[PDB]
Amino acid sequence: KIPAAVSNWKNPNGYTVALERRVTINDGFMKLSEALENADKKARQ
Amino acid sequence: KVMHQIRACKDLKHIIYYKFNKNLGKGPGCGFWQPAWRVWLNFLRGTIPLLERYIGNLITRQFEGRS
Amino acid sequence: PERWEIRQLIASG
Amino acid sequence: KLFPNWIKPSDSEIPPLLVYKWTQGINNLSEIWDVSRGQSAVLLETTLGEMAEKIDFTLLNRLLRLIVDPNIADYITAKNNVVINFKDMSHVNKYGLIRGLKFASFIFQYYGLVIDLLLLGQERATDLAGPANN
Amino acid sequence: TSHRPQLEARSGAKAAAYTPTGIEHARLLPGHTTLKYRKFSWRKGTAFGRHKGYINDMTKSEYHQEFLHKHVR
Amino acid sequence: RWNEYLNPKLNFTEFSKEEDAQLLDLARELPNQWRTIADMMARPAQVCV
Ligand SMILES: O=P(O)(O)O[C@H]1[C@H](OP(=O)(O)O)[C@@H](OP(=O)(O)O)[C@H](OP(=O)(O)O)[C@@H](OP(=O)(O)O)[C@H]1OP(=O)(O)O
């Protein structure tokens, strides 16, 4: 049951349609920023 | 590509006007037309079948029509 | 203006 | 006096005058062209390749808080993270310098400053820029 | 809606039914008229140093990344 | 106006305790990357600010 082919770029017959028919991390950043905070603490110490 | 033959005719001019005019300088009067005549006859030798095919296609478009 | 002429003097040679 | 002498384009010369001063300074070293005792001089040119495309904003923020007020550094690391629209596509530029920013010269020098300190080291850089009072 | 996709092709039955006109083309001139036949201490001040294939996707390939780093500078 | 207020697919509702306690951890982790935190939360950037 193929959907009825609604897209964003070309509306050929000028139909308006229901609006919804138009339209996590690695650990390493925790490894960087924490370490940078650590180094910043050492700098301030 | 007639320019080829035209250049050759100009080039034959540039030879013949400085072997016809050794003691004559500059001016009209030269009429040794033989090799430029040969060059244009060789051009016609080349474009007899060219014009046969071109005008055959044109005349059959005039009578028979476009395929 | 004084500072800019000293800066152009340092920058030139 | 943040940026040392070796960082270019400095405001003191046009790039042909940069080339001329560079050739003069190559000549004006003490016994540079002497090969009598068997010396050797090496001149190396290389591109710091993709330097504006691999700047990490955590590292960049911690580098920029050393030199400016941290409101400015938060502004800079939040300005280099905007959406890049185009005709069709769009993406959040999560890291890497957008060179088209007006102040993106400064970051491209300042981060480049870090690479100089990682190439010259500390001691020779202290030799090159001289003391701070002069 | 004056421009449309193709539903089916112009069939060669429609070209076989037409009577031909003799238009001697520039390329159907006789050429290659023979068929060939076969037989039958100074570096210890710094912070870094030595003292201290193929994938099928073309956009994700190695050559395409070499290309884009070659041609966007 | 579309991608920040009128697109219904991204969430404007009030955040849970989990989302606040992970957004503080992100704002420590990714300091001033508010479009990046917006992509991670699938939420509007200025709303998360
Ligand atoms: O302009 P010039 O460099 O002085 O050459 C001319 C020119 O020959 P080009 O075609 O090579 O330029 C004339 O040709 P046209 O101007 O007629 O095209 C030609 O005169 P004719 O063709 O009428 O014979 C004449 O030759 P001349 O005056 O000796 O007859 C010839 O001068 P040069 O002999 O000094 O090259």
Image (cartoon, grey):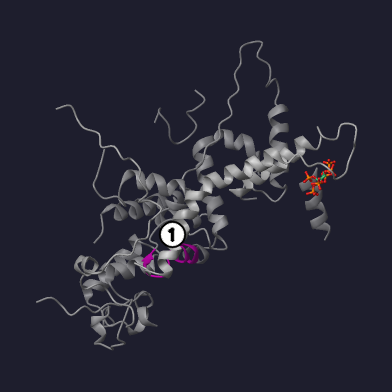
Q: Is residue D83 magenta?
A: yes
The chain letter under disc 1 is B
Residue A4: name its quadrant. bottom left
Res A14 quadrant in image: bottom left
- In the image, what residue type sits under mark 1? Gly
Measured as percent of width and height from the top left, residue D92 is found at 37, 65
- Using the image as rendered, state which of residue E30 and residue A5 is in the foreground: E30
Q: Quadrant of ligand 1?
A: top right
Give left or right: position of D37 versus E7. right
The structure residue drawn at horizontal position 37% and vertical position 49%, both measured from the top left corner, is: E29
Question: Does residue C12 appear to the left or right of F11 in the view shown?
Answer: right
Judge whether residue E56 is colored magenta: no
Identify which residue, D97 or D68, lies in the foreground.
D97
Q: Is residue D73 above or below residue E71?
A: below
Judged left or right of residue A42, residue F26 is left
Q: Looking at the figure, which quarter contains the C terminus of chain D?
A: top right
Which residue position is annotated with label 1?
Answer: B56
Element type at mark 1 = helix
The image shows residue D8 at horizontal and vertical percentages of 63, 46
Which residue appears at 70% of the width and 51% of the height?
D11
The furthest residue to the left? A1
| For residue E64, side relative to residue A20 (left or right) | right
Residue occupying the point 30% across, 75% down: F43
Q: Tell me where the magenta segment starts and ends, as one range.
A: D75-92
Where B66 falls versus E39 (above or below)? below
Residue D130 seen anywhere in this rendered image of the structure: yes
Q: Circle 1: is it few (<14), some (14-19), or many (20+) Cα within 10 Å?
A: some
Q: Pinpoint residue B5: horizontal percent, then vertical percent.
A: 63, 44
Evaluate whether residue D121 shows in this view: no
Specify the quadrant of the image occupied by residue E20: bottom left
> Which percent across, then down, holds residue A21?
23, 81
